[PDB]
Image 1: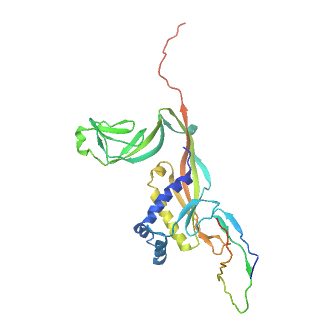
Image 2: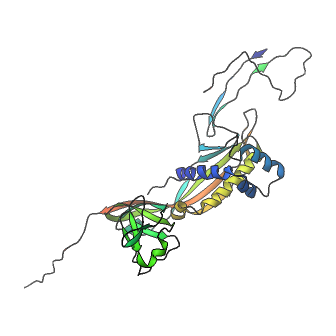
Image 3: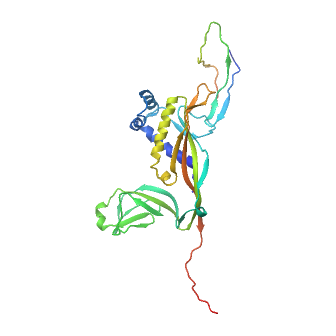
Length: 48
Length: 275
């Protein structure tokens, strides 16, 4: 499960940057670790 | 001649950086002091003609996303006026002159003279490579081409010379009014890998060293000084930090404007008086 998904944009001298918070909730017995990675094939995101 | 330091920096950096990254020998010479690991990783990533990864350079505040694997970032910085001349006078010219050009030109035979052709007319001839024309050669410039006596020099009919000269714009004359400006420009390399940033900074230093032989900054942007900042995390809000080490470059240039003169004396009216 995933919630609060945010595409926070910061415009800076280096350029634009995409960073935001998304809150997720797992199943039982699963022990996630720091800097684990997830990918959602179903959901597509537009970029230019 | 108003000076745009940023554009000059970009134009000098891009082809020179590409050429430096083209070959491995120069890069190995540059990165002699670095360890094997970082040196070889950078060479694998960026060095070579067939490199898959590539660096980029551009100005600050681009509305588009900018590649943060390896990039050179420029911003204009401060400026100050340091020295002035009397009446703000810098120089006087009889013929309007533009930029200083260097052109290769093979010698040619003309019925009385050996000559070199050039792309554009000549306002003033500074130097011909490895030549010191004497009175006998009677060096003369006639618009596009420069010429010297055929007979005693006939061994050199195809001399592969090159020429440093100046463009001609107009026959008018005027005064140069302006001052000197001491300007600071900031350059920083960006990379999420700190070692890549270090190597990028070293390459930047080398190309700055190499630039000092360039005609334009030899004539326009003397007194180059450098200053380096500390390695700092540029951004922390991403999934991974951006690391960069800003560098400050200083230059001295003469902002000036040509003030034309329409007064030309060609007659004299020396007459006495009576009482």
